[PDB]
Length: 305
Length: 305
Image (tube, rainbow over all chains, first blue to last red; front, side):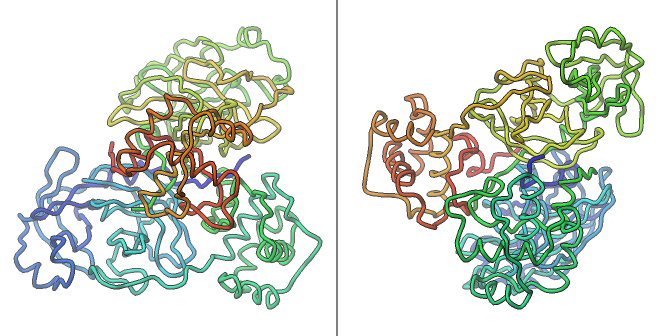
């Protein structure tokens, strides 16, 4: 037993990380088959980031201006193209460590692991959620751009995120692997600010199920509620409205524990209205929202890859 | 910026994980060079765990009774020995993926990453601390025994933990890679209970430094304190006494931020006596103690491996 914020094993992604240098800018790239994906702002200095015209800046870049290094060995760039906000650098060697993979555009509220990297080298791994305002709360220093987020199902890596920017608020924005930003954000150093950081209600409920499975039960009460009544409280607390689809998604956890979904909603309603009274749940003094219902089942049943 | 509980990249350890089956018991082993390390209780059924005589139970095991599988390929066991609470299974093939490595016995308060595995296959990775009562708060289901904890320095994996048992309280105990338990625990299903779960004071202070570096500063106050005065409060709150060695270890973080160690101790004293008043620090509503001073510098300076 025990429940921890757990990232996927990162070995399959470590083997895909490269360093991409263009002029004086170095960030990370993702090498899959004979293509390296990286943020298009690798072509920019920090001064260019205030109002870049990427098509114009790219005119002055040729294949040989993109230096790509896998460990200590140089790859040969034989073509390049801009797709949305990423560059695709065609190299002459397919990555021998390419895993089975897919590119997926995740929905807000879903979770993924991030392999934070610098100069093409892995630093660490941690689990994130795509927030309802389309930011993530990561750990990214200068040079971490191009680090990726992913999920693994058995032997297949589903890449869902590439890091591009930090906002002045200290939160993080980026694209899918087709280069389309999550949310309204752009790869320019501007006044762009995140909206309300709403709480992912279905995930909180999943984590309360995880708590019950792992022995934390003090918050179970004698009440029930309805979706409409619960949502009147969710709105007050800046929680996402809970839908019938969410109830359905909690079905397996409800069956495993014998606690009806709406009974758990009534427990959450009380926790929102009365606080935790100095108590903890699964070692946390706040209501955790970065575990999906699938994450909870995965960890509680020991799924491997 | 941003500060997250971050595990080491796990690829180097993933390549060392194997499945070890003896009779009807299957757990994980660690394959380094031509040796596989695993918990000696692989020789036990759950019924044997109440009062095992491991030397007697081992008499009835031969090399061929230990089935070792690396992925889908079987390794050949050519010798076995018991060292403390681990078995060393000599195999006829050195692991081609063996990293540079060391075995280290960590001190209470130090942190490490755990690669949780089942049937020799990785499930996930997360960061733990060796608690002052010599337990860890992990995520381990049946079959996770033999999963290991480690640190990485550049290219060298320092293995420090192997998982053996879960106590009835739901906390986790295990050995170093020489097979010696951390703390007073034994590999028997008995009444053994953990002592007081004291808070790792130096780590809390390190995390408060990390908070200041990353913009959370509301808890900085106008007070200072002394080691002896602070420790009168630490004792009340079941915090480890802070020593001069701890002050020295916080020196680099103190220099980076310009906040004297004893000034940060005064901030912590106020947080202990008055609580957080519903506020948060680095996304937590409790005082986090599983980041060492080294961990904070590592993450804030982007150290890679």
